[PDB]
Image: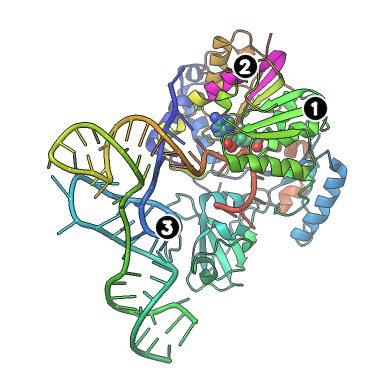
RNA sequence: AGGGUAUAGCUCAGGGGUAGAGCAUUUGACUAGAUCAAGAGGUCCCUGGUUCAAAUCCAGGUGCCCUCUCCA
Protein backbone atom coordinates (compact mmCIF):
# COMPACT_ATOMS: atom_id res chain seq x y z
CA UNK A 1 0.00 0.00 0.00
CA UNK A 2 1.82 3.05 1.36
CA UNK A 3 5.49 1.99 1.44
CA UNK A 4 7.65 0.83 -1.50
CA UNK A 5 9.49 -2.50 -1.72
CA UNK A 6 12.28 -3.31 0.74
CA UNK A 7 15.41 -1.49 -0.44
CA UNK A 8 17.86 -4.33 -1.07
CA UNK A 9 21.29 -4.46 -2.69
CA UNK A 10 21.02 -5.72 -6.30
CA UNK A 11 23.12 -8.77 -5.43
CA UNK A 12 21.02 -9.55 -2.33
CA UNK A 13 17.70 -9.15 -4.13
CA UNK A 14 19.02 -11.36 -6.93
CA UNK A 15 20.14 -13.88 -4.30
CA UNK A 16 16.68 -14.10 -2.77
CA UNK A 17 15.30 -14.15 -6.32
CA UNK A 18 17.46 -17.20 -7.02
CA UNK A 19 15.94 -18.66 -3.87
CA UNK A 20 12.28 -18.16 -4.76
CA UNK A 21 12.64 -18.97 -8.47
CA UNK A 22 14.28 -22.40 -8.29
CA UNK A 23 13.52 -25.25 -10.71
CA UNK A 24 10.94 -26.94 -8.49
CA UNK A 25 8.83 -23.84 -7.81
CA UNK A 26 9.00 -22.84 -11.48
CA UNK A 27 7.88 -26.36 -12.38
CA UNK A 28 4.96 -26.37 -9.95
CA UNK A 29 3.84 -22.78 -10.59
CA UNK A 30 5.55 -21.18 -13.58
CA UNK A 31 7.88 -18.18 -13.81
CA UNK A 32 5.07 -15.67 -14.42
CA UNK A 33 3.52 -16.65 -11.08
CA UNK A 34 6.59 -17.26 -8.91
CA UNK A 35 8.08 -13.89 -9.88
CA UNK A 36 4.90 -12.07 -8.87
CA UNK A 37 4.89 -14.03 -5.61
CA UNK A 38 8.46 -12.90 -4.90
CA UNK A 39 7.74 -9.27 -5.76
CA UNK A 40 4.59 -9.37 -3.62
CA UNK A 41 6.73 -10.59 -0.73
CA UNK A 42 9.27 -7.80 -1.22
CA UNK A 43 6.35 -5.36 -1.29
CA UNK A 44 4.88 -6.75 1.93
CA UNK A 45 8.09 -6.82 3.98
CA UNK A 46 8.09 -3.01 4.21
CA UNK A 47 4.78 -2.83 6.07
CA UNK A 48 4.07 -3.61 9.75
CA UNK A 49 2.06 -6.71 10.68
CA UNK A 50 -1.65 -5.86 10.86
CA UNK A 51 -1.89 -7.29 14.38
CA UNK A 52 -0.20 -6.41 17.65
CA UNK A 53 0.13 -9.82 19.32
CA UNK A 54 0.66 -10.00 23.09
CA UNK A 55 1.65 -13.08 25.08
CA UNK A 56 0.01 -13.43 28.49
CA UNK A 57 2.15 -14.55 31.44
CA UNK A 58 -0.19 -17.29 32.64
CA UNK A 59 2.06 -17.94 35.65
CA UNK A 60 1.14 -14.60 37.23
CA UNK A 61 -2.17 -13.62 35.62
CA UNK A 62 -4.91 -15.31 33.61
CA UNK A 63 -5.76 -14.29 30.05
CA UNK A 64 -9.17 -12.92 31.10
CA UNK A 65 -7.73 -10.60 33.77
CA UNK A 66 -4.94 -9.36 31.51
CA UNK A 67 -7.47 -8.80 28.70
CA UNK A 68 -9.64 -6.65 30.95
CA UNK A 69 -6.67 -4.63 32.22
CA UNK A 70 -5.55 -4.14 28.62
CA UNK A 71 -9.07 -2.99 27.77
CA UNK A 72 -8.73 -0.29 30.42
CA UNK A 73 -5.24 0.51 29.11
CA UNK A 74 -6.42 0.88 25.50
CA UNK A 75 -9.26 2.99 26.86
CA UNK A 76 -6.64 5.32 28.36
CA UNK A 77 -4.11 5.42 25.50
CA UNK A 78 -6.54 5.90 22.62
CA UNK A 79 -8.61 8.52 24.49
CA UNK A 80 -11.65 6.25 24.35
CA UNK A 81 -11.37 4.66 20.91
CA UNK A 82 -12.84 1.22 20.21
CA UNK A 83 -10.34 -1.44 19.14
CA UNK A 84 -11.10 -5.08 20.03
CA UNK A 85 -8.84 -7.53 21.86
CA UNK A 86 -9.35 -10.98 20.36
CA UNK A 87 -8.14 -14.22 21.94
CA UNK A 88 -6.54 -16.80 19.65
CA UNK A 89 -8.44 -20.13 19.58
CA UNK A 90 -5.32 -22.18 18.83
CA UNK A 91 -2.79 -20.20 20.86
CA UNK A 92 -4.59 -20.14 24.21
CA UNK A 93 -2.33 -17.58 25.91
CA UNK A 94 -2.08 -15.06 23.06
CA UNK A 95 -4.09 -11.84 22.66
CA UNK A 96 -4.61 -10.02 19.36
CA UNK A 97 -5.10 -6.26 18.85
CA UNK A 98 -5.78 -4.89 15.34
CA UNK A 99 -3.59 -2.15 13.85
CA UNK A 100 -5.35 1.00 12.65
CA UNK A 101 -3.45 2.16 9.57
CA UNK A 102 -2.08 3.38 7.36
CA UNK A 103 -3.21 7.00 7.69
CA UNK A 104 -2.33 8.99 4.57
CA UNK A 105 -3.96 12.22 5.77
CA UNK A 106 -1.25 13.19 8.26
CA UNK A 107 -0.14 16.79 7.71
CA UNK A 108 3.64 17.09 7.80
CA UNK A 109 5.04 19.74 10.15
CA UNK A 110 8.16 21.84 9.52
CA UNK A 111 9.95 20.90 12.73
CA UNK A 112 11.48 17.53 11.88
CA UNK A 113 13.24 14.70 13.70
CA UNK A 114 15.11 11.66 12.40
CA UNK A 115 15.39 8.34 14.24
CA UNK A 116 17.33 5.15 13.58
CA UNK A 117 15.87 2.58 11.20
CA UNK A 118 15.30 0.18 14.09
CA UNK A 119 13.65 2.94 16.14
CA UNK A 120 11.45 3.73 13.15
CA UNK A 121 10.42 0.10 12.80
CA UNK A 122 9.60 0.18 16.51
CA UNK A 123 7.48 3.31 16.07
CA UNK A 124 5.50 1.73 13.22
CA UNK A 125 4.71 -1.10 15.64
CA UNK A 126 3.25 1.40 18.09
CA UNK A 127 6.23 2.61 20.10
CA UNK A 128 7.11 6.16 21.14
CA UNK A 129 10.52 7.67 20.39
CA UNK A 130 12.79 7.41 23.42
CA UNK A 131 15.94 9.55 23.73
CA UNK A 132 18.52 6.97 22.58
CA UNK A 133 16.64 6.66 19.29
CA UNK A 134 16.89 10.22 17.97
CA UNK A 135 19.90 10.64 15.68
CA UNK A 136 18.89 13.99 14.18
CA UNK A 137 16.59 16.95 14.86
CA UNK A 138 15.79 20.48 13.72
CA UNK A 139 18.15 22.84 15.56
CA UNK A 140 15.23 25.07 16.54
CA UNK A 141 13.31 22.29 18.28
CA UNK A 142 11.98 23.10 21.75
CA UNK A 143 10.32 20.74 24.22
CA UNK A 144 6.64 20.71 23.31
CA UNK A 145 6.92 21.33 19.57
CA UNK A 146 4.63 19.19 17.42
CA UNK A 147 7.27 17.52 15.26
CA UNK A 148 7.26 15.08 12.35
CA UNK A 149 9.27 11.90 12.90
CA UNK A 150 11.14 10.42 9.93
CA UNK A 151 12.91 7.05 9.72
CA UNK A 152 16.50 6.91 8.44
CA UNK A 153 15.85 3.55 6.78
CA UNK A 154 19.30 3.46 5.16
CA UNK A 155 21.07 4.33 8.41
CA UNK A 156 23.11 7.01 6.69
CA UNK A 157 22.39 9.99 8.94
CA UNK A 158 25.47 10.92 10.96
CA UNK A 159 24.34 11.62 14.53
CA UNK A 160 23.73 15.23 15.51
CA UNK A 161 23.26 16.50 11.96
CA UNK A 162 20.98 19.49 11.36
CA UNK A 163 20.11 18.45 7.80
CA UNK A 164 19.70 15.18 5.90
CA UNK A 165 19.54 14.72 2.13
CA UNK A 166 19.28 10.94 2.37
CA UNK A 167 16.25 8.65 2.36
CA UNK A 168 13.58 9.48 4.94
CA UNK A 169 10.26 7.77 5.63
CA UNK A 170 7.39 9.59 7.35
CA UNK A 171 6.29 7.76 10.49
CA UNK A 172 3.86 10.36 11.81
CA UNK A 173 3.70 13.32 14.18
CA UNK A 174 4.42 13.60 17.89
CA UNK A 175 4.93 16.00 20.80
CA UNK A 176 8.62 16.40 21.63
CA UNK A 177 9.70 16.46 25.28
CA UNK A 178 13.32 17.44 24.67
CA UNK A 179 15.08 20.24 22.79
CA UNK A 180 17.86 19.45 20.31
CA UNK A 181 20.24 21.03 22.81
CA UNK A 182 19.27 18.69 25.67
CA UNK A 183 19.87 15.76 23.32
CA UNK A 184 23.06 16.71 21.50
CA UNK A 185 24.72 19.20 23.89
CA UNK A 186 27.71 17.61 25.61
CA UNK A 187 27.35 13.85 25.94
CA UNK A 188 24.68 12.84 28.45
CA UNK A 189 23.71 9.22 27.75
CA UNK A 190 20.23 10.27 28.83
CA UNK A 191 17.14 8.06 28.88
CA UNK A 192 13.38 8.59 28.97
CA UNK A 193 10.74 9.99 26.62
CA UNK A 194 11.85 11.99 23.59
CA UNK A 195 8.89 12.16 21.22
CA UNK A 196 5.34 11.24 22.26
CA UNK A 197 3.71 9.95 19.07
CA UNK A 198 0.28 11.56 18.74
CA UNK A 199 -0.46 10.90 15.06
CA UNK A 200 1.36 7.77 13.83
CA UNK A 201 0.88 6.32 10.34
CA UNK A 202 0.05 3.00 11.98
CA UNK A 203 -1.83 3.23 15.28
CA UNK A 204 -0.75 0.55 17.76
CA UNK A 205 -0.65 0.57 21.60
CA UNK A 206 2.53 1.51 23.49
CA UNK A 207 3.84 -1.45 25.50
CA UNK A 208 6.59 0.15 27.59
CA UNK A 209 5.76 0.12 31.30
CA UNK A 210 2.31 -1.49 31.04
CA UNK A 211 1.76 -4.71 33.01
CA UNK A 212 5.43 -5.78 32.82
CA UNK A 213 4.79 -8.88 34.94
CA UNK A 214 1.76 -10.03 32.96
CA UNK A 215 2.64 -9.22 29.34
CA UNK A 216 5.29 -10.07 26.79
CA UNK A 217 5.21 -8.47 23.36
CA UNK A 218 5.88 -11.37 21.02
CA UNK A 219 5.25 -12.13 17.35
CA UNK A 220 2.58 -14.79 16.75
CA UNK A 221 4.86 -17.47 15.27
CA UNK A 222 7.39 -16.88 18.06
CA UNK A 223 4.65 -17.55 20.58
CA UNK A 224 3.67 -20.55 18.47
CA UNK A 225 7.12 -22.15 18.70
CA UNK A 226 6.94 -22.83 22.44
CA UNK A 227 3.54 -24.42 21.89
CA UNK A 228 4.90 -26.60 19.07
CA UNK A 229 7.77 -27.79 21.28
CA UNK A 230 5.09 -28.87 23.78
CA UNK A 231 7.07 -28.94 27.04
CA UNK A 232 5.62 -31.04 29.86
CA UNK A 233 5.93 -30.03 33.54
CA UNK A 234 8.98 -31.67 35.12
CA UNK A 235 11.00 -32.19 31.94
CA UNK A 236 14.45 -30.86 31.07
CA UNK A 237 14.40 -28.28 28.29
CA UNK A 238 17.27 -26.38 26.68
CA UNK A 239 17.25 -23.60 24.09
CA UNK A 240 20.80 -23.00 22.84
CA UNK A 241 20.09 -19.48 21.57
CA UNK A 242 17.73 -17.92 24.08
CA UNK A 243 18.22 -14.19 24.74
CA UNK A 244 16.37 -12.09 25.57
CA UNK A 245 14.36 -15.15 26.60
CA UNK A 246 10.90 -14.78 25.10
CA UNK A 247 10.48 -18.40 24.09
CA UNK A 248 12.45 -19.37 27.21
CA UNK A 249 10.06 -17.70 29.64
CA UNK A 250 7.20 -19.01 27.52
CA UNK A 251 8.49 -22.58 27.86
CA UNK A 252 8.85 -22.03 31.60
CA UNK A 253 5.28 -20.74 31.81
CA UNK A 254 3.92 -23.70 29.84
CA UNK A 255 5.53 -26.06 32.36
CA UNK A 256 3.89 -24.19 35.25
CA UNK A 257 7.47 -23.38 36.33
CA UNK A 258 7.79 -27.05 37.32
CA UNK A 259 10.95 -28.57 35.85
CA UNK A 260 14.27 -27.32 34.51
CA UNK A 261 14.82 -24.83 31.69
CA UNK A 262 18.45 -24.19 30.75
CA UNK A 263 18.99 -21.14 28.54
CA UNK A 264 22.32 -20.42 26.85
CA UNK A 265 23.68 -17.37 25.03
CA UNK A 266 26.98 -16.09 23.63
CA UNK A 267 26.75 -12.44 24.72
CA UNK A 268 26.84 -11.60 28.45
CA UNK A 269 24.46 -8.63 28.57
CA UNK A 270 21.91 -10.70 26.66
CA UNK A 271 22.08 -13.47 29.28
CA UNK A 272 21.58 -10.80 31.92
CA UNK A 273 18.47 -9.77 29.99
CA UNK A 274 17.25 -13.38 30.12
CA UNK A 275 17.71 -13.43 33.89
CA UNK A 276 16.00 -10.05 34.27
CA UNK A 277 13.02 -11.29 32.25
CA UNK A 278 12.73 -14.57 34.17
CA UNK A 279 12.93 -12.77 37.51
CA UNK A 280 10.40 -10.21 36.27
CA UNK A 281 7.72 -12.64 35.09
CA UNK A 282 8.16 -14.86 38.14
CA UNK A 283 9.64 -17.96 36.52
CA UNK A 284 12.12 -19.86 38.71
CA UNK A 285 12.82 -22.91 36.54
CA UNK A 286 14.95 -20.74 34.25
CA UNK A 287 18.73 -20.91 34.54
CA UNK A 288 20.72 -18.78 32.09
CA UNK A 289 24.39 -19.11 31.15
CA UNK A 290 26.82 -17.16 28.97
CA UNK A 291 28.19 -19.93 26.76
CA UNK A 292 28.97 -20.91 23.16
CA UNK A 293 26.25 -23.29 21.99
CA UNK A 294 28.55 -24.89 19.43
CA UNK A 295 30.83 -26.06 22.25
CA UNK A 296 28.10 -27.16 24.67
CA UNK A 297 28.76 -30.90 24.39
CA UNK A 298 30.93 -32.40 27.15
CA UNK A 299 34.29 -33.69 25.89
CA UNK A 300 36.96 -33.34 28.59
CA UNK A 301 36.96 -34.80 32.11
CA UNK A 302 35.50 -32.50 34.78
CA UNK A 303 25.23 -28.48 36.80
CA UNK A 304 26.83 -25.80 34.62
CA UNK A 305 27.57 -26.18 30.89
CA UNK A 306 28.86 -28.01 28.96
CA UNK A 307 26.41 -30.90 29.32
CA UNK A 308 26.66 -34.65 28.79
CA UNK A 309 25.23 -35.96 25.49
CA UNK A 310 21.62 -37.21 25.60
CA UNK A 311 20.81 -35.39 28.84
CA UNK A 312 17.94 -33.12 27.79
CA UNK A 313 14.28 -34.04 27.32
CA UNK A 314 13.59 -31.28 24.80
CA UNK A 315 15.76 -28.84 22.82
CA UNK A 316 14.80 -25.59 21.10
CA UNK A 317 17.19 -24.32 18.44
CA UNK A 318 15.93 -20.81 17.74
CA UNK A 319 19.06 -20.38 15.62
CA UNK A 320 20.46 -16.94 14.69
CA UNK A 321 19.40 -15.95 11.17
CA UNK A 322 19.46 -13.24 8.50
CA UNK A 323 16.20 -11.85 9.86
CA UNK A 324 14.83 -11.27 6.36
CA UNK A 325 11.34 -12.05 7.63
CA UNK A 326 11.38 -9.00 9.90
CA UNK A 327 8.46 -6.60 9.48
CA UNK A 328 8.57 -3.78 9.01
CA UNK A 329 11.92 -3.92 7.21
CA UNK A 330 11.99 -1.05 4.72
CA UNK A 331 15.70 -1.37 3.85
CA UNK A 332 18.62 -3.78 4.26
CA UNK A 333 22.15 -2.63 3.43
CA UNK A 334 23.76 -6.05 3.89
CA UNK A 335 26.32 -7.84 1.75
CA UNK A 336 25.28 -11.18 0.26
CA UNK A 337 28.16 -12.81 2.13
CA UNK A 338 26.58 -11.42 5.31
CA UNK A 339 23.11 -12.77 4.49
CA UNK A 340 24.38 -16.27 3.67
CA UNK A 341 26.82 -16.25 6.61
CA UNK A 342 24.53 -18.18 8.94
CA UNK A 343 24.08 -21.69 7.50
CA UNK A 344 27.37 -23.06 8.90
CA UNK A 345 26.72 -21.69 12.40
CA UNK A 346 23.15 -23.01 12.32
CA UNK A 347 24.49 -26.42 11.30
CA UNK A 348 27.05 -26.45 14.12
CA UNK A 349 24.43 -25.47 16.68
CA UNK A 350 22.14 -28.12 15.18
CA UNK A 351 24.75 -30.87 15.54
CA UNK A 352 25.43 -29.81 19.12
CA UNK A 353 21.68 -29.92 19.73
CA UNK A 354 21.21 -33.42 18.30
CA UNK A 355 24.11 -34.70 20.40
CA UNK A 356 22.52 -33.18 23.51
CA UNK A 357 19.12 -34.78 22.91
CA UNK A 358 17.69 -37.81 24.72
CA UNK A 359 16.10 -40.59 22.64
CA UNK A 360 12.38 -40.02 21.97
CA UNK A 361 13.12 -36.35 22.64
CA UNK A 362 11.88 -33.36 20.67
CA UNK A 363 14.07 -30.89 18.77
CA UNK A 364 12.40 -27.75 17.43
CA UNK A 365 14.40 -25.74 14.90
CA UNK A 366 13.09 -22.25 14.18
CA UNK A 367 14.19 -19.15 12.25
CA UNK A 368 12.70 -15.74 11.45
CA UNK A 369 14.14 -15.69 7.93
CA UNK A 370 12.62 -16.55 4.55
CA UNK A 371 15.66 -18.00 2.75
CA UNK A 372 15.76 -21.65 1.64
CA UNK A 373 19.38 -22.12 2.72
CA UNK A 374 18.50 -21.41 6.35
CA UNK A 375 15.19 -23.29 6.42
CA UNK A 376 14.12 -26.21 4.19
CA UNK A 377 17.71 -26.92 3.11
CA UNK A 378 18.74 -27.18 6.76
CA UNK A 379 15.87 -29.62 7.32
CA UNK A 380 17.00 -31.80 4.41
CA UNK A 381 20.60 -31.62 5.60
CA UNK A 382 19.49 -32.51 9.13
CA UNK A 383 17.46 -35.50 7.96
CA UNK A 384 20.42 -36.66 5.86
CA UNK A 385 23.35 -36.26 8.28
CA UNK A 386 21.31 -37.40 11.28
CA UNK A 387 19.27 -40.53 10.40
CA UNK A 388 18.06 -40.89 13.99
CA UNK A 389 16.06 -37.69 13.61
CA UNK A 390 12.64 -37.87 11.96
CA UNK A 391 10.38 -35.00 10.90
CA UNK A 392 7.20 -34.71 12.98
CA UNK A 393 3.81 -33.07 12.40
CA UNK A 394 3.09 -30.03 14.58
CA UNK A 395 0.34 -28.66 16.82
CA UNK A 396 -1.03 -26.14 16.39
CA UNK A 397 -0.77 -25.99 12.59
CA UNK A 398 -1.17 -22.32 11.68
CA UNK A 399 1.35 -21.21 9.06
CA UNK A 400 1.70 -22.40 5.48
CA UNK A 401 3.56 -25.51 4.37
CA UNK A 402 7.22 -25.70 3.36
CA UNK A 403 8.65 -24.14 0.21
CA UNK A 404 9.69 -26.38 -2.68
CA UNK A 405 13.38 -26.42 -3.59
CA UNK A 406 15.20 -28.44 -0.93
CA UNK A 407 14.19 -31.74 -2.53
CA UNK A 408 11.75 -32.68 0.22
CA UNK A 409 8.50 -34.54 -0.48
CA UNK A 410 5.06 -32.96 -0.21
CA UNK A 411 4.43 -35.14 2.84
CA UNK A 412 7.60 -33.69 4.38
CA UNK A 413 6.71 -30.12 3.41
CA UNK A 414 3.25 -30.40 4.99
CA UNK A 415 4.97 -31.10 8.31
CA UNK A 416 6.90 -27.82 8.23
CA UNK A 417 5.49 -24.44 9.25
CA UNK A 418 6.52 -21.56 6.97
CA UNK A 419 4.88 -18.17 7.48
CA UNK A 420 4.53 -16.14 4.29
CA UNK A 421 4.20 -12.33 4.39
CA UNK A 422 2.80 -12.53 0.85
CA UNK A 423 -0.02 -14.87 1.90
CA UNK A 424 -2.82 -12.30 2.04
CA UNK A 425 -3.17 -8.70 0.76
CA UNK A 426 -2.26 -5.79 3.04
CA UNK A 427 -5.34 -4.74 5.05
CA UNK A 428 -5.66 -0.96 5.32
CA UNK A 429 -7.69 -1.10 8.52
CA UNK A 430 -9.80 1.86 9.64
CA UNK A 431 -12.65 2.12 12.16
CA UNK A 432 -15.26 1.49 9.46
CA UNK A 433 -13.35 -1.65 8.47
CA UNK A 434 -13.16 -2.64 12.14
CA UNK A 435 -16.91 -2.36 12.69
CA UNK A 436 -17.91 -4.41 9.63
CA UNK A 437 -15.34 -7.17 10.14
CA UNK A 438 -16.17 -10.84 10.61
CA UNK A 439 -14.05 -12.39 13.37
CA UNK A 440 -12.95 -15.35 11.26
CA UNK A 441 -11.48 -12.80 8.85
CA UNK A 442 -9.51 -11.09 11.62
CA UNK A 443 -8.11 -14.39 12.91
CA UNK A 444 -6.95 -15.49 9.45
CA UNK A 445 -5.45 -12.02 9.07
CA UNK A 446 -3.52 -12.50 12.31
CA UNK A 447 -2.33 -15.93 11.20
CA UNK A 448 -1.30 -14.94 7.67
CA UNK A 449 -0.21 -11.29 7.69
CA UNK A 450 2.75 -11.89 10.00
CA UNK A 451 6.54 -11.74 9.98
CA UNK A 452 8.67 -14.26 8.13
CA UNK A 453 9.11 -17.39 10.22
CA UNK A 454 9.98 -21.08 9.91
CA UNK A 455 9.35 -23.96 12.33
CA UNK A 456 10.53 -27.57 12.01
CA UNK A 457 9.92 -30.42 14.47
CA UNK A 458 12.17 -33.44 15.01
CA UNK A 459 12.07 -36.59 17.15
CA UNK A 460 14.96 -38.88 18.10
CA UNK A 461 15.01 -42.69 18.15
C1' A B 1 31.42 -23.69 5.35
C1' G B 2 29.66 -18.70 10.28
C1' G B 3 30.01 -13.37 9.26
C1' G B 4 30.70 -8.00 10.08
C1' U B 5 33.43 -4.30 12.50
C1' A B 6 37.82 -1.24 15.06
C1' U B 7 39.88 6.08 12.10
C1' A B 8 38.89 12.91 16.32
C1' G B 9 34.99 13.52 22.47
C1' C B 10 30.13 11.54 19.66
C1' U B 11 28.30 9.59 14.61
C1' C B 12 30.82 7.96 10.39
C1' A B 13 33.33 8.65 5.18
C1' G B 14 37.93 7.69 3.05
C1' G B 15 42.31 5.29 1.52
C1' G B 16 49.98 1.91 -0.61
C1' G B 17 53.13 7.85 0.49
C1' U B 18 51.42 15.54 3.73
C1' A B 19 44.64 12.70 8.36
C1' G B 20 38.76 13.83 6.37
C1' A B 21 33.18 15.47 7.11
C1' G B 22 28.76 16.44 10.40
C1' C B 23 27.80 17.30 15.56
C1' A B 24 29.82 18.39 20.24
C1' U B 25 33.72 21.47 22.51
C1' U B 26 37.05 26.20 22.41
C1' U B 27 37.74 31.37 20.79
C1' G B 28 36.13 36.09 18.46
C1' A B 29 32.24 39.17 16.50
C1' C B 30 26.84 40.44 16.16
C1' U B 31 21.79 40.88 18.66
C1' A B 32 21.76 33.28 26.23
C1' G B 33 21.66 31.97 20.38
C1' A B 34 17.30 28.95 13.95
C1' U B 35 23.38 34.74 13.28
C1' C B 36 28.73 35.18 11.22
C1' A B 37 33.79 34.03 11.53
C1' A B 38 38.05 31.64 13.29
C1' G B 39 41.17 26.48 15.40
C1' A B 40 41.64 23.68 18.67
C1' G B 41 41.56 17.07 17.59
C1' G B 42 43.82 11.09 15.95
C1' U B 43 50.71 6.16 17.42
C1' C B 44 43.89 5.29 12.23
C1' C B 45 43.01 -1.57 18.14
C1' C B 46 47.64 -5.14 19.14
C1' U B 47 51.11 -8.23 16.61
C1' G B 48 53.29 -10.35 12.43
C1' G B 49 53.49 -10.87 6.74
C1' U B 50 53.92 -8.69 1.63
C1' U B 51 56.30 -3.92 0.17
C1' C B 52 61.13 1.12 -1.06
C1' A B 53 57.07 2.44 1.99
C1' A B 54 51.01 -0.32 5.36
C1' A B 55 46.34 4.01 8.76
C1' U B 56 45.23 1.44 3.79
C1' C B 57 46.40 -5.16 1.33
C1' C B 58 47.04 -10.26 3.99
C1' A B 59 47.18 -13.60 8.56
C1' G B 60 46.64 -14.27 13.75
C1' G B 61 45.08 -12.03 18.39
C1' U B 62 41.47 -9.20 21.19
C1' G B 63 37.06 -6.00 22.08
C1' C B 64 31.97 -4.83 20.25
C1' C B 65 28.00 -6.43 17.13
C1' C B 66 24.69 -10.10 13.77
C1' U B 67 16.60 -7.09 16.52
C1' C B 68 13.66 -12.50 16.25
C1' U B 69 8.13 -6.51 18.97
C1' C B 70 9.26 -0.73 22.52
C1' C B 71 15.28 3.38 25.81
C1' A B 72 16.95 1.13 19.39
N1 LIG C 1 27.07 -19.66 18.93
C1 LIG C 1 25.92 -19.08 19.58
N2 LIG C 1 25.61 -19.84 20.64
C2 LIG C 1 24.55 -19.50 21.44
N3 LIG C 1 23.82 -18.39 21.16
C3 LIG C 1 24.13 -17.61 20.07
C4 LIG C 1 25.18 -17.94 19.29
N4 LIG C 1 25.27 -17.01 18.31
C5 LIG C 1 24.28 -16.10 18.49
N5 LIG C 1 23.57 -16.46 19.58
C6 LIG C 1 22.43 -15.79 20.15
O1 LIG C 1 21.09 -16.18 19.35
C7 LIG C 1 20.24 -15.22 19.64
C8 LIG C 1 19.19 -15.06 18.53
C9 LIG C 1 17.92 -14.44 19.13
N6 LIG C 1 17.14 -13.90 18.13
C10 LIG C 1 17.13 -15.53 19.86
C11 LIG C 1 15.69 -14.99 20.22
C12 LIG C 1 15.03 -15.92 21.24
N7 LIG C 1 14.86 -17.20 20.68
C13 LIG C 1 13.68 -15.36 21.63
O2 LIG C 1 12.64 -15.84 21.13
O3 LIG C 1 13.61 -14.43 22.45
C14 LIG C 1 21.11 -13.98 19.72
O4 LIG C 1 20.66 -13.17 20.70
C15 LIG C 1 22.54 -14.51 20.04
O5 LIG C 1 23.03 -13.93 21.33
Q: Secondary structure at mark 2?
A: helix
- Is residue A349 covered in magenta? yes
Q: CA distance from mark 1 to mark 2?
A: 21 Å
- For this rendering, which residue is in front, A275 or A320? A275
Q: Crowding near pointer 3: few (<14 within 10 Å), some, many (20+)?
A: few
- Figure check: A212 above or below A334: below
Q: Disc 1 designates what residue?
A: A259
- For this rendering, which residue is in front, A261 or A113? A261
Q: Disc 2 designates what residue?
A: A354
Where is residue A260 shown, x and y percent of the image?
76, 28
Q: Secondary structure at mark 1?
A: loop
Where is residue A202 shown, x and y percent of the image?
63, 52
Where are the magenta residues, as a range?
A346-365
Q: Secondary structure at mark 3?
A: loop
Which mark sits nearer the N-terminus, 2 or 3?
3
Q: Residue at x 48, y 23 (%)?
A: A344
Q: Are marks 1 and 3 in contact (CB under 8 Å)?
A: no
- Numbered circle sitting on residue A158: 3
- Is residue A331 covered in magenta? no
- Figure check: A22 above or below A103: above
- Parent chain of label 2: A
Amino acid sequence: SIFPKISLRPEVENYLKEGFMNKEIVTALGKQEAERKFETLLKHLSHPPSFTTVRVNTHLASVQHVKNLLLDELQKQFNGLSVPILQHPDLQDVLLIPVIGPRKNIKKQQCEAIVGAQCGNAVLRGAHVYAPGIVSASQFMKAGDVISVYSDIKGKCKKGAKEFDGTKVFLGNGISELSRKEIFSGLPELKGMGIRMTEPVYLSPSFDSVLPRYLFLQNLPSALVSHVLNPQPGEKILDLCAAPGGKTTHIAALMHDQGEVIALDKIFNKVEKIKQNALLLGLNSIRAFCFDGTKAVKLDMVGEPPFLPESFDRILLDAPCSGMGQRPNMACTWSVKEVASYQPLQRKLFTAAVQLLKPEGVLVYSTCTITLAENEEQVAWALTKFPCLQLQPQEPQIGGEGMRGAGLSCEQLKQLQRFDPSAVPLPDTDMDSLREARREDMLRLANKDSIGFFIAKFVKC
